[PDB]
Amino acid sequence: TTGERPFSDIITSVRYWVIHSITIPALFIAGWLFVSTGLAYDVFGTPRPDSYYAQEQRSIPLVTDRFEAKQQVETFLEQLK
Amino acid sequence: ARRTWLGDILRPLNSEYGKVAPGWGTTPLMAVFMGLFLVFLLIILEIYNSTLILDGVNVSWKALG
Amino acid sequence: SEGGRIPLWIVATVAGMGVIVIVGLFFYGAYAGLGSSL
Amino acid sequence: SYPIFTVRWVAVHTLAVPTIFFLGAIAAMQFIQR
Amino acid sequence: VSGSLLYGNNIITGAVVPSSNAIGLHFYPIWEAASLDEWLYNGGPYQLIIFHFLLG
Amino acid sequence: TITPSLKGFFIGLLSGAVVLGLTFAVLIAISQIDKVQRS
Amino acid sequence: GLPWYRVHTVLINDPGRLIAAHLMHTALVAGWAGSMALYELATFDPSDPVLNPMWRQGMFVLPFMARLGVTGSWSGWSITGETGIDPGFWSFEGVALAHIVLSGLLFLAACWHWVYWDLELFRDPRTGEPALDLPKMFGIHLFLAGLLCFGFGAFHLTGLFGPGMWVSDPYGLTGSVQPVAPEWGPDGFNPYNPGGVVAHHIAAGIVGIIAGLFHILVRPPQRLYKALRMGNIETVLSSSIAAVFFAAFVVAGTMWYGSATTPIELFGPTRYQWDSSYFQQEINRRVQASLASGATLEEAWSAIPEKLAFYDYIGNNPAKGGLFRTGPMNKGDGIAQAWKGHAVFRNKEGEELFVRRMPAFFESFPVILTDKNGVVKADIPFRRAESKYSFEQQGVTVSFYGGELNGQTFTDPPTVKSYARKAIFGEIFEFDTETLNSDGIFRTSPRGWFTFAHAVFALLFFFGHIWHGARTLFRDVFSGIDPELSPEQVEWGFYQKVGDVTTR
Amino acid sequence: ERGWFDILDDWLKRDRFVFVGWSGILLFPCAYLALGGWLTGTTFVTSWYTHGLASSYLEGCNFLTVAVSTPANSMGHSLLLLWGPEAQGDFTRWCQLGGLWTFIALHGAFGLIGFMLRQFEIARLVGVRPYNAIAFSAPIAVFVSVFLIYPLGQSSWFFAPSFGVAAIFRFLLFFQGFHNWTLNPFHMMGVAGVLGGALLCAIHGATVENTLFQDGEGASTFRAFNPTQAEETYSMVTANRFWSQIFGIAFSNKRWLHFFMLFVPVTGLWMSAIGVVGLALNLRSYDFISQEIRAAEDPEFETFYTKNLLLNEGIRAWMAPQDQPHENFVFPEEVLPRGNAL
Amino acid sequence: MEPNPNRQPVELNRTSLYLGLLLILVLALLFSSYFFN
Amino acid sequence: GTFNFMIVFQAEHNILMHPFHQLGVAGVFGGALFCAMHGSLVTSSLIRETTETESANYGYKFGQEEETYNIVAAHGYFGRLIFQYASFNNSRSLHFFLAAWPVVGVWFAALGISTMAFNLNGFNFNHSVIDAKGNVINTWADIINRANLGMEVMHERNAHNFPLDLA
Amino acid sequence: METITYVFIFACIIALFFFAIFFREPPRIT
Ligand code: CLA
Ligand code: CLA
Ligand code: CLA
Ligand code: CLA
Ligand code: CLA
Ligand code: CLA
Ligand SMILES: CC1=C(/C=C/C(C)=C/C=C/C(C)=C/C=C/C=C(C)/C=C/C=C(C)/C=C/C2=C(C)CCCC2(C)C)C(C)(C)CCC1
Ligand SMILES: CC1=C(/C=C/C(C)=C/C=C/C(C)=C\C=C\C=C(C)\C=C\C=C(C)\C=C\C2=C(C)CCCC2(C)C)C(C)(C)CCC1
Ligand SMILES: CC1=C(/C=C/C(C)=C/C=C/C(C)=C\C=C\C=C(C)\C=C\C=C(C)\C=C\C2=C(C)CCCC2(C)C)C(C)(C)CCC1
Ligand SMILES: [Ca+2]
Ligand SMILES: [Ca+2]
Ligand SMILES: [Cl-]
Ligand SMILES: [Fe+2]
Ligand SMILES: [Mg+2]
């Protein structure tokens, strides 16, 4: 043994579960709201199901310039009206 | 072992086997040069890569003429 | 605080059921909403 | 008798905290409709 | 399909070619053919080889 | 002249120096606080 | 006895025979250089620098000789296409011969160091045992390397005392050996600026001199001496192998992407010049400038140099080859004889049509023609029964401007299709496929082969480095671990610090 | 000597549950960021702007189809640093441009270096020979060759494998259709080494497990072993006679057996690495010229090689327009290669 | 001349011979197709 | 011909997208990993019985009773490389794992082929992802699909008279 | 010539099998 508290002791202890019956569900709910509020989409720039294409467009918004790529993308996002 | 004229001339350049400077000696200075060299490779890399773009530095066959 | 209060076989059974539930939810989600092909 | 905050503890949580966050996120994702 | 060395294959391209689709799952031993020339045309070696192999 | 990308380069360099710096500082601190027992 | 893969280890403690072995090696490499150069001169046709330059002929060492200023033969020709030049002794032949003689002299020296291995020079005067003081050898060698680097940059490359180096226009049309002044500004780190190469060798040269003096005069720290086992020559082997694979990946990269030391007239064009249609853009620029100044279409295209059109042809793309497709590019598509001229496609309505070019990725590629806006107007169909775009339906025609076919128009679908098939490759050329029994399948250039070989060897030297670093650092345990190794040294918690007995 | 360095060394090399080491300083952040980047990307990040693909659970992908996809072809080989000239410090745009790909590839790489250094460090401290690290050189050669050298020889990071299950399958089929990669003898050696390593793993495990000495009364024989026992747990003599009579040859030397077990998969992976490096330059084993000359003159001449080339031609034409969107391929129905009916 | 003491005998046992011949022959069988091309 | 069989199989069954073949891959890749691993650790823990001018193999003599490496040291290494309880201290358990992993995996590969033999095929996520309008949003699965289509349409180019390949 | 070569190499391999089995160095317990 290397000196740290054994895992079976910790996770069979009451205190561990007092702490984690709070912290685990809290994290779970936080992830949930991260998606459900739509925040994930905004942070990562992932299209919502209605933001992949303009209404009549069938062409992929493929990035075609290395150094103006940011601008190209912004223009693509603008063209979603 | 065989001695030779040239062997006698070069003897001192190979007579200090095992000889060390005390402790860490010049290690920190070396370390500074390593940091600077790392930074240099990083610079020339990013120039070549066009991640670092410098005025008058046109990374292309069309560099001048 | 005291090690041993909540028996290890219960912790394992509950955690395991949790895993079954969450994975089960992901498999449900394969048939509904995005990625469902519908 | 035993320390609490060890290297092992940090390592465990660097993996475990985001894992639960992400599992929660994906769970939420199963209910998104086009 | 040419599978053999003498008929223009090297080690990488070469094969003993599978029996004819016309045979299907029919058992095609040498003696069911009117000739060895026929047996070879229809890929009897494949069947003889794979069955003896699998048994072995 | 300092182009936007040279500024970017400097930002990356600083970011790296910060990461490694805070890292070694913390590790040194911890090593000093938590010495091995000898003899 | 010794296992086979260890036979050379007898040299580890035999500096004289190790030196002998290095001499043999050096002799072998130099003999190779000589033999390769002679073979290349014996097969090389200097008659057409335009369409049959060295890089089409599988020349490998010839371009490196040219790169540093050897451009002529004693027989009177030059790789730039001049006649009646006297190159002096330092023709390609002179280089080869010099290398052969060097090789030989190194062989004899190898023999001397092998027989007379037991020189007092190689013995530690205090212990009488064989020993090499590697840190100081390093300093001496570093100093010499430095002097040589400096002198190379300052004298050879500047032309101050030397020929200079190969430099060219951006499109590899007018290359020659020129003196090059060092670039001391930021553009010196531009891979495409040669002056950067000169400044590099001069400055790095001085740095090598200084660091070398430093290494002659200043002993290693005890801590570094012990940590890197600097008394063990194998450590030097390990780190040297590491530096060498590093350098090899570097020359591989600059070969593949192109640089001022990897010029297209010596090694061929890059795959990327094809990717961005670099020569096509320049050709079009020149043609447009020609039309703008009042030239006819025919005149405008005839003014395009054949060499430039040849660079705009995928057969010269180094990314079109095959690993077992051996030899010169000429063995494949043939010896290029002439540009046919620019093929222009048109349909029955007279709209200009454009063939979709084959990307390097595709061994085969369909034939597709679009209008200037990329709308499909014609193709060579696979299934015909529902074809709507056949050249026959669309009455596709082709007219040639410039080259051998200048002014001609073909309207019969078979011929127009043939030229379209060739047009996917870009500009179309006449080839001699008979002389070499060319088989018609693209081969890579010396650029591709160099890049391949060096990337591979570099990658294997990564293993070499790993292996020898391990041997250096684990010398104590390479016949096996301590038979008296205590289980407590490996049982958890017994020591607070792994492997440290003083921490029970 | 007892300065801060040696004290730091002391703490770093403490015998704890998860060893850290000097190697840990490189390994752990880099491995953590690599893994984290992969999970983050696979959960939340699109490939719409780089590939015209969905690639996250958020978009409806599953574990099999999610990926962190390569950057757009137009990015070339940009390191694509967050603070680089493309993204200009904007994390969202950086995500949308595929910055996470280069993030994962490069941190992955420094991470593997950290792992191998770790193997070395621990080997030195424990007093074993560092063959585990040496064997680990093979995974690295594969990673470096496939994820770095390969795309660097091509047009851009775009054509590297994307970090995703399905993305990886696509990468395999691409290599078939374009490189005819199965035909490459370096790949064939890779295969032989993988299948050979698995064979040796299975056959040695089964052989040890079936020549055990009876060292306990239990019918479950696992307890009848003690880590510290001097004696061999299985009969080498019996194993040898068995295989000698069954297969014709057999091991008689355990040290050789195990070195061979090191040698085979490692050498295989390394060979494969060499082949893929070749593919970086399209220097393929695509064809046999003799085959082509014969088939071109003789339309009755057919081999499995020619059949596979037809397959290859199909893959290339049918997958290319969507797989390589930057080329703006439009292949009319009539040009698509097809056999009868299908 | 006074003999060199660094000399070592060299060995290849039979098992090693068989292994080497196997390696070389099978490699040749593999690559031969490509050499003939 | 083997490669042919493989390519056509991918076309007709999407074997790559079949979990049993993926299990086959974890199996053979894993088998190799563990083979190299075991090889390396055992080689790493050979007891010094030889000199540097001779092969370490001569340190083991055929049929000797004593083990030729130190498993406690091996375990000491590998247990620190990952963490203690992720390492085998039991040679019988370790070798059983070595037997079982590739064998079970390859059983699954074999069963993959054996079940795709009856046309229960790989996962089909073609057009699984759809936007708000109903536009198809390609995934990597769909690019795979395009490759499969190429394979499908070109193979046995003269064998089909009818539009579907039903066997 | 190709065919001759391939078959030659193969035959060399089978003969090698033969020698490797029946004419191996015998394993001896020390
Ligand atoms: C030691 C562990 C480690 C390592 C090896 C890396 C390595 C890498 N990371 Mg980093 N990363 C790490 C930890 C690490 N990371 C951590 C913990 C985080 C969380 C904050 C990140 C977050 C991160 C991000 C967000 C990103 C990276 C990226 C990068 C890459 C480029 C970094 C660079 O350009 O720095 C340059 C700086 C140095 C090399 C330091 C030089 C130090 C010298 C010796 C001292 C000189 C500095 C001097 C004092 C400054 C004076 C300047 C003055 C003149 C103005 C690189 C592959 C990028 C990437 O991968 O993009 C694809 C990227 O976007 N990393
Ligand atoms: C005696 C002097 C001499 C001269 C004048 C030449 C000249 C010539 N030889 Mg060379 N050659 C020589 C000796 C010489 N050789 C010897 C002794 C050998 C045997 C090893 C060879 C083997 C050789 C071969 C195999 C080949 C040549 C070739 C050539 C020609 C092109 C050279 C070139 O491309 O170099 C390139 C050299 C470098 C790029 C040197 C790199 C230096 C590294 C990076 C140094 C790193 C270590 C250093 C200590 C780092 C610190 C530096 C410090 C300053 C900071 C050229 C005509 C080529 C030729 O075309 O064949 C016909 C060719 O292929 N030579
Ligand atoms: C840096 C090394 C190098 C490079 C880049 C070149 C490049 C060039 N050579 Mg030169 N050549 C070289 C070294 C090199 N050569 C050497 C050392 C020799 C002396 C033998 C020659 C002799 C030579 C001749 C005689 C000729 C060339 C020609 C040419 C060109 C044709 C290339 C060719 O067809 O490749 C073919 C490459 C291959 C088929 C790849 C070989 C791969 C091997 C067989 C792999 C071996 C695998 C191994 C056994 C596996 C072990 C596994 C084990 C560890 C388990 C080409 C430009 C030709 C040319 O056109 O010149 C005018 C020409 O005729 N070369
Ligand atoms: C300058 C580079 C260099 C040097 C000086 C050495 C030197 C040494 N290494 Mg080597 N090594 C290197 C690079 C280098 N290595 C690299 C890059 C690798 C990775 C591929 C290795 C891998 C390696 C291993 C795995 C081993 C060594 C060992 C040895 C030692 C004995 C060599 C011997 O007896 O072989 C005798 C060799 C033969 C009798 C025939 C070899 C035939 C080769 C495989 C094929 C033909 C090669 C061809 C002639 C060379 C062309 C030149 C090439 C550069 C293109 C020796 C001290 C051995 C050792 O440590 O023993 C204690 C050992 O086990 N090395
Ligand atoms: C898998 C990779 C790997 C591994 C396992 C080793 C392992 C070994 N090497 Mg190293 N080595 C490597 C790669 C590797 N090397 C590379 C790529 C080089 C460059 C030439 C070297 C150069 C080298 C030398 C010169 C020496 C060693 C030595 C050694 C040994 C001692 C350990 C040490 O020195 O580490 C060295 C430390 C590292 C490899 C870690 C470097 C981490 C860097 C600094 C992070 C940089 C971050 C970067 C700036 C971010 C920007 C990225 C950019 C793309 C944007 C050991 C056997 C020594 C030896 O053999 O002694 C007997 C020795 O003298 N190695
Ligand atoms: C018998 C069938 C067969 C076999 C045995 C193989 C086996 C091989 N093929 Mg494959 N291949 C096949 C058929 C087959 N192939 C077919 C039919 C095709 C279609 C043409 C391909 C196409 C193909 C390609 C295109 C490639 C391969 C590759 C390889 C090799 C993969 C080696 C590997 O482990 O890399 C796995 C990766 C590594 C070892 C890198 C390091 C990995 C690190 C250590 C991972 C660390 C993970 C970390 C702990 C976190 C995990 C997090 C978790 C959440 C995931 C190997 C030789 C590759 C190869 O050749 O590489 C050189 C490759 O590029 N093959
Ligand atoms: C990138 C980013 C970075 C970093 C970040 C990070 C670091 C994060 C982390 C995070 C992570 C770390 C993630 C999480 C996770 C996991 C998940 C995502 C979930 C899961 C699980 C599972 C699902 C399981 C299941 C299965 C299997 C697998 C096993 C067993 C069986 C079963 C069925 C159970 C930063 C920010 C700096 C900046 C830039 C960006
Ligand atoms: C511990 C273990 C763990 C976990 C496990 C688990 C989590 C599992 C489970 C399960 C569970 C979760 C429990 C159970 C079972 C159930 C049953 C079996 C019952 C019975 C029922 C019936 C029989 C009845 C029916 C009837 C009729 C029929 C109709 C109507 C009415 C009724 C309903 C009544 C693990 C593995 C991780 C590890 C190891 C150990
Ligand atoms: C002695 C004497 C003499 C003579 C010298 C001579 C007669 C010359 C030589 C030398 C020689 C004339 C020889 C040589 C060189 C060559 C070699 C050394 C090469 C090698 C090759 C290699 C090594 C490669 C390998 C390869 C293969 C084959 C295939 C592919 C892959 C590779 C690349 C790997 C004199 C008068 C000077 C005077 C002094 C002394
Ligand atoms: Ca809706
Ligand atoms: Ca002919
Ligand atoms: Cl087929
Ligand atoms: Fe074993
Ligand atoms: Mg769903």
Image: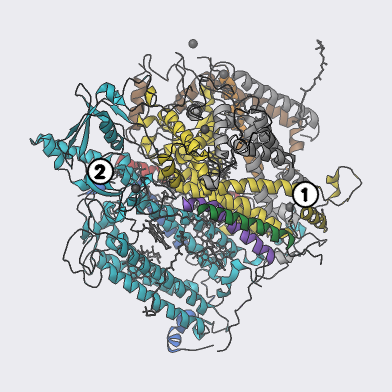
Chain colours: A brown, B blue, D orange, F red, G cyan, H yellow, I purple, K green
Residue A76 appearing in the image: yes
The three-letter code of the residue at mark 2 reads: Phe
Density class for disc 1 (Cα within 10 Å; few <14, some 14-19, many ≥20) is many
Element carrying mark 1? helix
**Chain of the residue under label 1:** H
Who is closer to the viewer here, F9 or G338? G338
J47 over G17 or under it: above or below: above
Structural crowding at the residue carrying mark 2, measured as other residues with C-alpha within 10 Å and reported as few (<14), some (14–19) or many (≥20): many
Q: Position of residue G380 (x, y in %)?
A: 33, 28
List the single residue furthest toward the left: G294
Say left or right for F16 vs H212: left
Find residue G183 and report its horizontal and vertical position in percent: 25, 57
F4 lies left or right of C33: left
Residue occupying image coordinates x 50% and y 79% = G16
Residue closer to the observer: G264 or G253? G264
Q: CA distance from mark 1 to mark 2?
A: 65 Å
Residue G246 locus on image (x, y percent) = 44, 57
Tell me where residue G6 appears, x and y as whole percent.
60, 68
Using the rendered image, report if marks 1 and 2 lie on a common chain.
Answer: no
Left or right placement of residue J118 versus residue G224 in this view: right
> Circle 2 is placed at which residue position?
G429
At a point 73% along the width and 38% down the height, the residue shown is A7
- Disc number placed over residue H207 in the picture, else none: 1
Displayed quadrant of residue H231: bottom right
The residue under the point 56% across, 57% down is H4
Image mark 2: chain: G
In the image, which is nearer the foreground, mark 1 or mark 2? 2
